[PDB]
C-alpha cells in the first residue's frame, strides 16, 4: 500500500541526513577488494546484532571480526572492519522500514568504494541480476566524484527487463524488498576519461534467528 514502508512497489528512495566529517575521508583508507572487481573496488565490512530494547529503542552489538572432508558448508570472504560509525544510517533504515520489533536482526554493513578511469570501468554487479539474500537492503550513495553510470535497476523475478531504473546521487539511498525484487547496477564510468570514484554503503537487514 501507499502508506506502507516500501510503498506500492517494494522500494523507496529517500534523502539522507548530512554525515559526519570523518566519513567521506575514510573511503580513502579502504583496502582493495581482492575477491571481485579487478582492482576497482575497495571495501570494509562490519556486522551488528540489533535487539529491541527499552521503550522503542534498539540495542546493537558489533560482531567479532576442518579435520575431515566436509559434506556441506560455506565459503566466506574476509574483510577488514569498518573504522567509522554508520549506525546513524542504520537508524535511518530502521525508521523507514518500520523494522519489526518482534525479534533481533542481523545488520550487515558494506563500505564500498568503486574507482573508474578512462578505459577502465568499475563493475558493480558483474554477476548480473541477483538477490542479496536478505529481507531488506539499503544502498546509500555518499560520494560521487567524476563518474557516470552506476544506475540501480530493480527487476521482478522472472522479468526480461527492469521495471524501475534510477541513477542515485550522493545524499540519496534506495531501500528495497530484497526478496520480492532483484537488482543489478550498471558499471561506474569515468566522466571525463580521468580517475573517478563512487562511495556507497550497503546496509542489509535479516532476522537474526534466520541466519543463526
Image (cartoon, grey):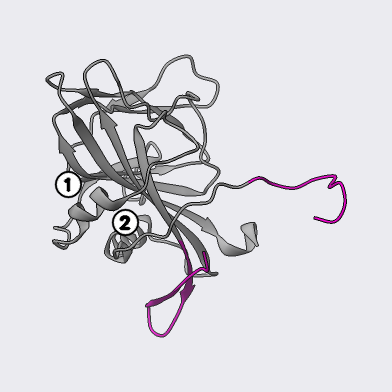
Find the residue positioned furthest to the right: 68
Which percent across, then down, holds residue 128?
47, 23
Q: In this image, 168 relative to 182: left or right?
A: left
Quarter of the picture containing the N terminus is: top left
Tag 2 secondary structure: helix
As drawn, the residue found furthest toward the bottom would be 54
Where is residue 200? Give x, y as percent: 29, 44
The range drawn in magenta is: 47-75
- Residue 171: assigned label: 1
Q: Which residue corresponds to mark 2?
A: 96
Q: Is residue 54 left or right of residue 64?
A: left
Q: In the image, is residue 88 above or below residue 123?
A: below
Please tell me which of labels 2 and 1 falls first in the chain: 2
Give the quarter of the image for residue 96. bottom left
Q: Which mark is residue 180?
A: none
Vertical position of residue 42 compared to residue 84: above or below: above
Q: Nearer the viewer, residue 87 or 120?
A: 120
The location of residue 87, given as percent across then percent down, is 32, 65
Main SS class of the magenta portion in the image: loop
Q: Position of residue 74 (x, y in %)?
A: 69, 46
Count how many numbered circles sit on residues in the image: 2
Residue 206 within the segment the image draws in magenta: no
Residue 71: within the magenta? yes
Residue nearest the observer in this picture, 131 or 41:
41
Q: Secondary structure at mark 1?
A: loop
Cα distance in 3D space between marks 2 and 1: 15 Å
Q: Residue at x 44, y 56 (%)?
A: 80
Mark 1 surroundings: few (<14), some (14-19) or many (≥20) residues within 10 A = some
Q: Residue at x 17, y 46 (%)?
A: 171
Quarter of the figure with residue 209: bottom right
| Mark 2, other Cα within 10 Å: few <14 / some 14–19 / many ≥20 | some
Amino acid at each position: 500500500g501507499s502508506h506502507m514502508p516500501l510503498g506500492t512497489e517494494g522500494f523507496t528512495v529517500i534523502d539522507l541526513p548530512e554525515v559526519a566529517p570523518d566519513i567521506l575521508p575514510s573511503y580513502d583508507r579502504c583496502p582493495v577488494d581482492d575477491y571481485m572487481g579487478n582492482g576497482t573496488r575497495f571495501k570494509r565490512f562490519s556486522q551488528y546484532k540489533l535487539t529491541p530494547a527499552e521503550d522503542d529503542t534498539w540495542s546493537f552489538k558489533r560482531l567479532p571480526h576442518k579435520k575431515f572432508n566436509p559434506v556441506g558448508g560455506g565459503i566466506r570472504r574476509v574483510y577488514e572492519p569498518i573504522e567509522v560509525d554508520f549506525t546513524p544510517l542504520i537508524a535511518e533504515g530502521i525508521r523507514e522500514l518500520g523494522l519489526d520489533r518482534s525479534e533481533p536482526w542481523q545488520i550487515n554493513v558494506h563500505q564500498n568504494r568503486t574507482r573508474a578511469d578512462g578505459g577502465r570501468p568499475g563493475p558493480l554487479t558483474p554477476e548480473g541480476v541477483h538477490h542479496d539474500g536478505h529481507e531488506f537492503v539499503m544502498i546509500a550513495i555518499l560520494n560521487k566524484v567524476n563518474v557516470a553510470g552506476g544506475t540501480t535497476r530493480l527487476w521482478k523475478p522472472g522479468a526480461d527487463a527492469p521495471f524501475w531504473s534510477g541513477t542515485l546521487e550522493a545524499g540519496q539511498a534506495v531501500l528495497l524488498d530484497d526478496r520480492g525484487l532483484a537488482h543489478d547496477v550498471t558499471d561506474v564510468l569515468s566522466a571525463d576519461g580521468g580517475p573517478g570514484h563512487r562511495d556507497i554503503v550497503i546496509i542489509a537487514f535479516s532476522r537474526w534467528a534466520e541466519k543463526w
